[PDB]
Amino acid sequence: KFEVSDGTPYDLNVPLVGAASFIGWVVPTLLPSQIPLYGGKGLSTAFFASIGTNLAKFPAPPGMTDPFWLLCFIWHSGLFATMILGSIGYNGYAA
Amino acid sequence: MTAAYLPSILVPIIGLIFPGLVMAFAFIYIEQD
Amino acid sequence: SHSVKVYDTCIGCTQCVRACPCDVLEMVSWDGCKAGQIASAPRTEDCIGCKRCETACPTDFLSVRVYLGGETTRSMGLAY
Amino acid sequence: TLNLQIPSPTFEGSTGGWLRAAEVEEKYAITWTSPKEQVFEMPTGGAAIMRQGENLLYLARKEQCLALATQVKNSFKITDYKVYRIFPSGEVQYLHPKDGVFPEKVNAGRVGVGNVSHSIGKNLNPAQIKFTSKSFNG
Amino acid sequence: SQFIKPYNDDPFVGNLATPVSTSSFTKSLLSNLPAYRAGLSPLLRGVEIGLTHGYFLVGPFYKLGPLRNSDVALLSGFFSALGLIIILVACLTIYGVVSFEETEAKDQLQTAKGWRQFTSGWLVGSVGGASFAYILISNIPFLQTAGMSML
Amino acid sequence: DVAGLTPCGESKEFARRLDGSVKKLQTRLKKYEAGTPPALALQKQIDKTKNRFDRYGKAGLLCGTDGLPHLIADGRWSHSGEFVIPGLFFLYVAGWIGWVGRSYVLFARTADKPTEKEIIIDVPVALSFVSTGFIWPFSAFKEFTSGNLIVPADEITVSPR
Amino acid sequence: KKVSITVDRDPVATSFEKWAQPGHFSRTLAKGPKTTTWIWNLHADVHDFDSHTNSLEDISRKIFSAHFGQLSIIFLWLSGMYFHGARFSNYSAWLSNPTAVKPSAQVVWPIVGQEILNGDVGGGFQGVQVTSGFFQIWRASGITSEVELYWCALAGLLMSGLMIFAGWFHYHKAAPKLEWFQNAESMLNHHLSGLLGLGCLSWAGHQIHISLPVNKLLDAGVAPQEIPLPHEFLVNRDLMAQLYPSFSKGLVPFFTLNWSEYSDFLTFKGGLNPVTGGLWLSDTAHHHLALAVLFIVAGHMYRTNWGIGHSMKEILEAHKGPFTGEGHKGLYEILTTSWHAQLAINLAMMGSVSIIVAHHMYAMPPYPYIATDYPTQLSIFTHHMWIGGFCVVGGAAHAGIFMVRDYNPAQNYNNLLDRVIRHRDAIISHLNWICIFLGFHSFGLYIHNDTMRALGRTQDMFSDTAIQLKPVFAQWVQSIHTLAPGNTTPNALATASYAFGGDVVAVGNKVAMMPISLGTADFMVHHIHAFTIHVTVLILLKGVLFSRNSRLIPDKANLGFRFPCDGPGRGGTCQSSAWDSVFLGLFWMYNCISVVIFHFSWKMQSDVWGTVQADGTVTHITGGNFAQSAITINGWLRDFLWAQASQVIQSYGSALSAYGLIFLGAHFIWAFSLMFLFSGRGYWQELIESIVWAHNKLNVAPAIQPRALSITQGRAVGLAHYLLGGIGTTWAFFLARIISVG
Ligand code: CLA
Ligand code: CLA
Ligand code: CLA
Ligand code: CLA
Ligand code: CLA
Ligand code: CLA
Ligand SMILES: CC1=CCCC(C)(C)[C@H]1/C=C/C(C)=C/C=C/C(C)=C/C=C/C=C(C)/C=C/C=C(C)/C=C/C1=C(C)CCCC1(C)C
Ligand code: SF4
Ligand code: SF4
Ligand code: SF4
């Protein structure tokens, strides 16, 4: 019974929108590229590999020239765009 | 300087305590009915 | 409040009453002019002091005069 | 007499409406009757639709009410509007038109307030009335 | 499906009901804050608010003050926070002196006795929170270096 | 001479100013080929500088210790051409302009629409007026003495005192 | 069909009668003057067409023909620049030696000693040095002789005559109807595909067929007189294929989509040409060709007589959500009925584009030998920055004019405009708070640094050798753009600009472009820029949103867009109109653009521009003082204002003395403006009463009664002389400094 306003009950559909937007953004971004930023992997997989690499170096943050920041920014930008569009499509149309 | 303690005693008082008490009491005076 | 005076040079053209945004002025019966009416200011507690009435007055130097005085919530035009 | 049960124009609301001083110091009300539902501009910003029949609306200032009255007079030919002042105690003071006749028309019983019996050039000098409770008008 | 409605179903009040202003999350957070939470004396509202604000006040004074590169940086930062707390308590006191008439009602914040209780609670909470932050930064090297001790 | 100043034709600092100006133009002249238009222009500038300094040195102008001509304007006849005679020339031209403008204003007052005469000038009548201005002192004085220049104080609007 | 040509023939007779009736366009003004105020009013409302008549058709016809007149004036101006380049310039000598000949296309007559302004500009030439960059444009276009410049001047003059004839024809002989003007879809299709698309395509044609071979021969060292004429490059395909062998293959690779064959004259090289310091012209040719294709594609989007196409009303009305009510409904009617709304949008867009032009043109120099021409770079950056700021504020002004005049609440119920008006208080309050926050945490850093450096506490300052404010995001973006060639743009040989990082491109021992590092001072000045822009937005947006009414004045729309006040009541209602908000926002725009161009001038002189000497070291103009001095106001006052004004104040007796004279005169006009800005009308009217008594005593009082300027005119005159004085002072200071040291 989440009210989005004073008297406006609205279903946020956070599980569906989150899961569907995550899958619909991650799966197309599994397309590989041979550029050094990706390293032979897709955008999502290069991002996850960079997460593992930098978590193997805790305290020490990723450097400026490290591909982690660019991978994180592009991946989260596309994810946020997918989440916004998925929220619009599922909450509005619902069919 | 003779009585060299007097600047370090009086300058914080004159510059922080005097204006604070003046501003507080003037505020009370100008806002009371 | 502001003080609004109407002098006997008034010709009763009712322009100052029509120009008043705050309903301060009104026309009352008089015999001093050809129109048979003079402006009056019974409600100067609502006067904001905009001097639109003086702008509307056509007599050489004005018949209606606004003297700004003590400021109140109404005269300052405060919606808060 | 202000009927508090008069319906209001359909308005979506705005941040320009009345503040805490309306419920604490004084508030103003304007009522009018329209022949049809039609869109007018709010004096606080925004468009509202007045209903067919009676309309009651609340404002913070008398000038806002009279601006709305002038707008509905000159754009919709509505002249039956009434402006009231309401206090927090519940007292309603009828304001406009004060005697039922608009102030630009002469009405019997009105007495002149603030009338001076000479021209403006006949006022007294400030040095004449200094240290003295005489008015500058004489 | 409209998300913005007139505030309190009143189209002529100077406010709008928005998701930032009137959602369930906003209403829960605002009603659960100590300044608005039901069942609290004004003194305890003051205690909670003072604990929070006085606790976080130590940090900027300790890390950025003129004595920040000295061995007495934390002591100076806590003393600066205490001086700010005393100044703000004087501000609260003079606000309550000029703002409220002496009434029997004392269970509300916006009463004279209620504001005095709130000021007392805010002073005691602010001193306690600043002292707690001082203790934690004095005894934990992680807080002294803001995490750089891990590197 | 006057006020301790020296005549410019014998002041050494006047000569130093002339020499410095000529040298400053000649070092610019050195970078251009003879017969090029910049060379001719620079040589003409050198000639104008030399002629100006010669004329100023032979005019009885007084130079101070700075090396520049100083004008005397106390009324003495040995320096009447430095302020007094240019002053008479200005006063003649300015009285001409004022007289013809006043005459046009008084003509425009007689027209059907005076303001149209102010914004759209009657050019033949204005040219007649600007021709009339050569005898402006005598005409203006006769206008004054006949009561046609000054209007009395009871016919001019004034504010309440 | 629905989109058709409808015209009225001979609507307005061509006559000189109304030329003799000033104020004929206005019923108020046509009665003639009675006071001098009329005169000012006659020049003040004259091109305000909607206030003279209510017919939208007549207004649209006047607008169309006035636009033709402006195009005629612009073409005459261009023809003048080409002619003065042809006859009064050293352009051929500059073509022979670009690195040592200062461009000059103005020669003065000798009258009163002003012949000193004909400075020794090189090439055996004396004249006024010009900084508009026309020499570099003509070199990029392949103009090698002054005969071609004469022909260009003739073409400009002929186009000026054609435009002025078209204005007379399309107003006085064949005026289009209102239905012709109200085709937004057809106008957008034709102007996207035909104006921008075919224009880009034809300029790509000129670049590929003319500019590339002539500039390739020029960069190889061929003298301009031995280069073949452009038509010889057109007809001799062997001569063209000697430079670009793909021209031996003809147009077959284009039509068969074998486009990589054209890779020798359509490149994606990036960086700069090492010989000239400009962009590769092959890159510009592919750029303009790709833009032509994209624009022609975009010009087929909108619906016209045939059934295909988008309807913009449908597009607008479909985009609406739960936060926004009716959404973008009603905007098509506004933008097809109100000329002021279109002028607001287009002025805002043109101003933003001019600002983008200034940034992108300093950073990626597009013309040969323009990067090392530091006066040209500084002049064009400053000029297009000023034009952009003025146009953006004009967009706000004409938005306010739409809001007062053309806005109809009946046609605007619960759409985006109505909801913006209905939460204007929230908008303006949050903007006010963010402006105060930006002012404190940007300018108080400078104040804090002034105090710390004055108190002898250097370790307490905000600096790179002190408590640091690193611009980490911009540095990260610079690292990305430096790493981009071969990684995120794999087919680009070099970076988009060397300002992000890379090598020092130097031409003739002068830095064309080098990396522009960002430190604490760059952080502080970019957040100063953000503060000034947000405050200008606050003033202009508050004026637009409160143009019709407010809590103070509930009937402000009845008073109009431009009124002085509503009297001394309500405490005082001075400067309450939207016009007065534009009046204040012009001052704040001046402040913003002044700080922007000062940042540019100091940063380029300190960290980019300079001379390259042995061992590859770069000696900058001010020797890298920006990092330690631009963190304090004292450093800006001493090391930028005091230090770099030495050239304009010691310019007397040289060719740059006109800049010293203009410097003094602009200080004078700026100070003169404060008489109008600080004073009020009643004082001047009473002083004029005394002067009227003096003229009345001599019977010389004018028939047109002299009045003091109106309150709005007092504000406008003060603002105009203020802007002229300040901009002229910066103009003279910049130009004298950069001509002397660069
Ligand atoms: C492909 C057709 C086409 C083209 C090229 C243009 C071009 C232009 N229109 Mg436009 N217009 C068109 C169709 C077109 N329109 C249609 C169909 C409509 C009706 C819906 C309009 C309605 C319209 C209005 C209402 C207005 C314009 C305006 C303008 C000018 C904008 C200012 C500018 O950048 O000028 C600089 C650009 C130039 C190219 C300068 C040269 C100008 C001439 C006329 C170009 C002619 C090129 C010619 C077709 C081919 C010869 C080139 C070569 C082969 C010899 C510009 C000249 C505005 C203007 O300023 O009007 C005067 C304006 O107010 N247009
Ligand atoms: C980024 C991914 C994405 C995109 C592009 C779309 C696009 C669309 N969805 Mg959709 N959807 C998504 C994710 C996405 N969806 C997810 C994750 C869910 C599950 C929660 C849904 C559930 C959903 C439902 C239930 C329905 C839609 C519908 C629609 C269509 C119309 C409504 C709309 O949002 O128009 C958006 C309009 C556009 C995208 C075109 C305009 C283009 C401009 C430039 C905006 C695009 C922004 C940018 C370029 C996008 C980049 C994506 C990024 C990942 C790189 C439209 C084709 C409705 C429909 O009719 O389709 C059947 C419908 O019924 N969607
Ligand atoms: C003449 C008035 C005056 C005086 C005496 C001082 C004195 C001082 N200022 Mg300064 N200051 C003043 C005016 C004054 N200021 C003004 C007008 C401004 C605004 C521009 C500032 C802004 C300013 C900043 C921004 C900072 C100082 C700091 C300091 C301290 C110097 C560094 C140090 O060793 O602190 C060591 C500090 C301590 C050991 C803490 C002392 C705590 C005191 C004793 C508590 C007093 C409580 C209160 C006043 C009780 C009375 C309340 C009543 C008036 C209502 C010193 C106490 C710095 C500082 O350290 O602040 C603490 C600092 O950061 N000042
Ligand atoms: C017909 C021309 C005319 C005449 C005869 C006068 C006469 C006078 N003016 Mg006046 N004035 C005029 C035009 C004229 N004014 C105009 C057009 C302006 C507006 C700029 C003023 C502004 C003005 C001020 C502000 C003051 C005077 C003052 C004075 C008095 C002293 C002389 C002076 O200061 O001159 C100086 C005059 C000026 C600086 C302005 C003159 C502008 C031009 C050059 C004159 C107009 C020429 C006109 C175009 C001729 C057309 C004729 C043609 C059609 C045939 C004197 C009564 C002063 C005063 O009160 O002294 C007691 C004073 O303070 N006037
Ligand atoms: C595409 C450009 C464009 C167009 C077509 C318009 C068109 C219009 N504007 Mg707009 N405006 C623009 C840009 C534009 N503006 C910009 C960029 C600004 C910001 C400065 C404004 C600010 C603005 C305001 C604030 C107002 C208008 C108004 C108007 C209307 C009447 C203008 C008039 O009669 O002036 C007639 C022309 C003049 C008075 C000439 C002005 C001369 C200037 C001030 C001095 C020029 C100095 C020169 C460049 C250098 C001199 C130096 C030398 C002396 C040494 C008209 C609809 C007015 C209106 O009522 O609209 C309804 C109004 O109040 N506009
Ligand atoms: C140098 C002159 C100057 C300064 C400092 C200001 C300052 C300001 N103007 Mg302003 N203005 C100016 C000239 C100036 N103006 C001129 C010439 C015009 C003519 C057109 C205007 C027109 C104008 C308009 C139209 C608007 C402003 C606005 C603002 C405010 C912006 C918010 C801000 O930066 O907060 C931060 C405050 C500052 C940067 C002021 C200096 C404070 C520094 C950081 C030190 C503080 C130290 C501390 C207080 C010391 C205490 C000591 C104790 C003893 C008191 C701010 C109050 C806008 C506004 O009010 O809305 C936000 C706005 O809308 N101004
Ligand atoms: C991070 C987080 C994620 C993003 C979103 C976000 C929500 C905005 C953000 C939160 C930022 C902010 C909002 C984080 C929330 C922050 C606040 C500042 C935390 C305050 C804690 C106060 C306690 C510890 C002091 C407790 C008192 C102790 C026990 C005292 C004992 C004392 C008593 C009097 C008795 C005597 C003994 C002593 C010792 C003197
Ligand atoms: S000043 Fe304004 S409110 Fe007061 S009487 Fe005159 S018009 Fe009415
Ligand atoms: S406007 Fe002047 S003349 Fe007319 S009624 Fe009012 S006071 Fe009298
Ligand atoms: S000072 Fe001028 S602008 Fe201000 S209220 Fe008075 S007349 Fe109007």
Image: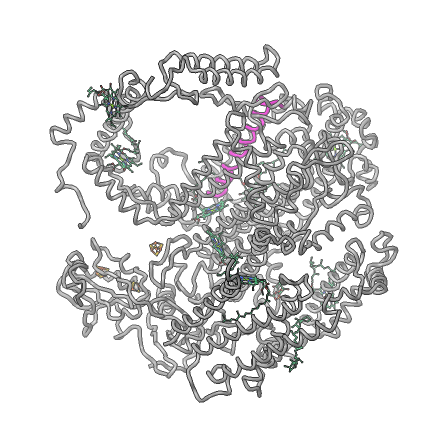
Question: Colour scheme of this structure image?
Answer: one colour
**Front-lying residue, G204 or C61:** C61
Above or below — where is E134 with respect to G257? below
Above or below — where is C67 with respect to G727? below
Can the viewer see residue G95 in this picture?
yes
Can the viewer see residue A8 in this picture?
no
Instruction: Single out the residue that lies furthest toward the front.
Output: B2
* Image side of residue G615 versus residue F39, left or right: right
Instruction: Single out the residue that lies furthest toward the left.
Output: F146
Above or below — where is G65 with respect to B15? above
**Magenta stretch in the rendered image:** G62-90
Q: Based on the picture, tell me whether residue G69 belongs to the magenta stretch.
A: yes
Using the rendered view, name the quadrant where residue G210 is placed: top right
Above or below — where is A59 with respect to G735? below
* Image side of residue C80 versus residue G463, left or right: left
Q: Position of residue A27 (x, y in %)?
A: 82, 64
* Image side of residue G124 versus residue G55, left or right: right
Using the rendered view, name the quadrant where residue E145 is placed: bottom right
* Image side of residue G586 versus residue F62, left or right: right
Q: Position of residue G278 (x, y in %)?
A: 71, 35
**Front-lying residue, B9 or C64:** B9
**Front-lying residue, G497 or G531:** G531
Q: Quadrant of ligand 10?
A: bottom left
What residue sits 26% from the left and 58% below the top? C54
Using the rendered view, name the quadrant where residue E65 is placed: bottom right
Q: Based on the picture, tell me whether residue D83 belongs to the magenta stretch.
A: no
**Front-lying residue, D62 or E120:** E120
